[PDB]
Image (cartoon, chains in turn orange, cyan):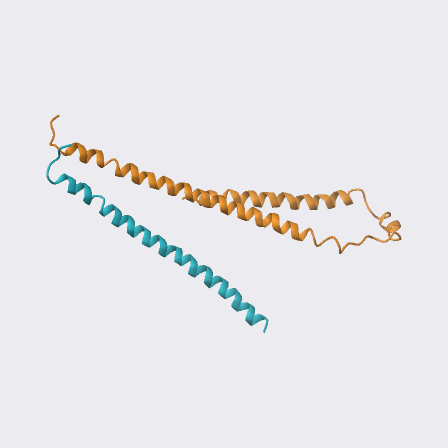
Length: 112
Length: 56
């Protein structure tokens, strides 16, 4: 299909610019997915950090019940007493895992 | 590779506009990273400010 002497080179060039420019958009996309990697890392590192401080206070402020105040406690205590206490400590843990995991699903809105 | 008398200047011009326009996007990017500098500054300055009142 006959054409002029310069048209075939205008048509090859208009698809070199497009591939180059669509090449830059890719490079920048990948960079922004690296920010959400740095961010997540930081957060989880600050949590693991606080843990190590707090668990390091409780070692020198320690005391035990005198041995004379046992005969008392072991006359009044039911069977479901200590089992109940443990529940109040397991419900706490569960809620902390729910909270951390709910904040990792919100990082899916950082790539928009 | 023989071409007409005006095609080589259409091809040089279509890459002058692109570099000029891609030049403006850079200028505006840098401005928006300056807003997040002003913002952070402000916040930390309001905290340091309250401290000085309360301890007084």
